[PDB]
Image 1 (cartoon, rainbow, N blue to C red):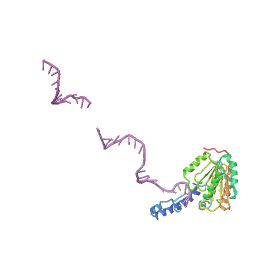
Image 2 (cartoon, chains in turn blue, brown):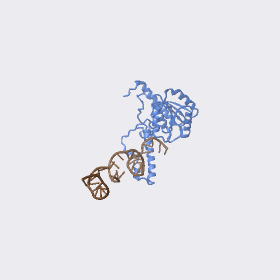
Image 3 (cartoon, rainbow, N blue to C red):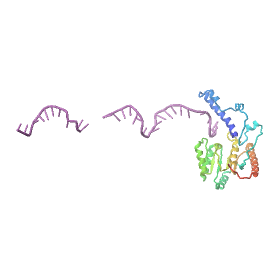
Image 4 (spheres, rainbow, N blue to C red):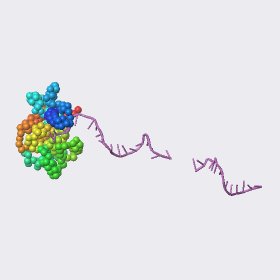
Length: 252
DNA sequence: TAGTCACATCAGTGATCAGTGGTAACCACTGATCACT
């Protein structure tokens, strides 16, 4: 499940653990048996697995290469969930528009998630945007469990309206009342900011009854536009399916 | 540098009971002085 971030997680975790295991065994901390005591490498994983089934919100490049591109699509939600609308704007000239949109939308008392690249201008935005009169919360690189479980509690208590985070946002931060999400200058190359994070934020906005993404780029890359195109076509398919399945949801 | 990434094991740390450390008659005596005839 969530293979798009599970298989890359397996690879990266194996790489990091084998690096630290070399740093241990070579520098006298553990035996090479501890190096053998490791998460499964992908070669031996393939050598050991049988009928392998993958499942994720997005088609992983490794899975697509392994399967040749032929997959099965079931991302359509009979429950009535659609992908978010997309607005693309330049990086500059956006703060006034954001303030106007949050003033117009705050009557619903929802939450808006924003992202940046590194810490300095991110925190500059945070203290400025708490200065001009909006309650804001931020995420850092060393977020512990309590400091955002309390964030979840106080957002279900409706104590603020906006969250900002760079990397501490893809792990279990589900919220039933997040409508608009802003992506700021993520077009630049990064080992931790390629297309999967943008599609993950798109899906996070999608899980709402009415999502929205505001995407700011100095330059346009093929990955983001292909992701937007596939998201839009999937949303069109979901809307077409839901137009026939007009029955209201009946949870059971 | 990303959320977890395997696996218990030492240190001297309060409060308090628990269970090692600290516990005048009798009138029996005999003598002195003495009340008595």
